[PDB]
Length: 99
Length: 99
Ligand SMILES: CC[C@H](C)CN(C[C@@H](O)[C@H](Cc1ccccc1)NC(=O)O[C@H]1CO[C@H]2OCC[C@H]21)S(=O)(=O)c1ccc(N)cc1
Image (cartoon, rainbow over all chains, first blue to last red; front, side, top):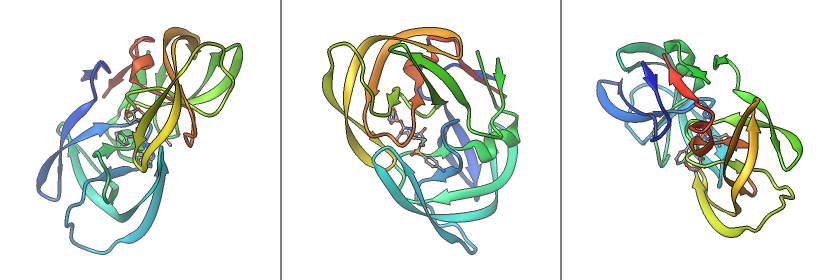
């Protein structure tokens, strides 16, 4: 589809058998999701933006479905104020910027 | 143009007669630039990102050309990790997400 940017580009996603809302964020290198208790191992990470850094848990090879488009890659989990789909997964669904 | 997301969507902008690089950031409501001298009146505001809130200077009705496309809108100036072009200007240049 085509998504205009008059409002936040929020879409439904499916991850670990849960449905959530997340932003398609070209400014996010990597996907970051609200605190959720995912299974399996993980590595600590720190990600920075406006205001400083937050600590997150990095899971790899996580399967996510975004508007029926499947992807699999890194998902960071932590106390983020918003769920964002980052470039690492936006590439996998063929998402482009156009003007 | 069409911009894929395998790398950061960085583009050259012209503001206050100066060239700079900036990130097209669909996850930003607002446009936030690193510290710089801008002619015009400004107002103190706060803006919050993933890591908390920062102090910025709000410049209204600023002319800014993004990748050869003119926009006139609000520009926040402050200690952001990187220049980001947010939706308030992305809408002006006709930018959409497509997959
Ligand atoms: C360094 C590039 C850019 C700032 C990075 N950010 C993504 C960005 O889209 C955030 C994503 C974001 C959206 C909402 C809350 C917190 C972060 N937007 C943002 O900070 O925008 C601010 C400016 O406009 C305002 O509207 C939104 C907040 C204000 S981020 O949230 O900090 C981020 C950093 C690393 C990863 N892997 C994923 C996300």
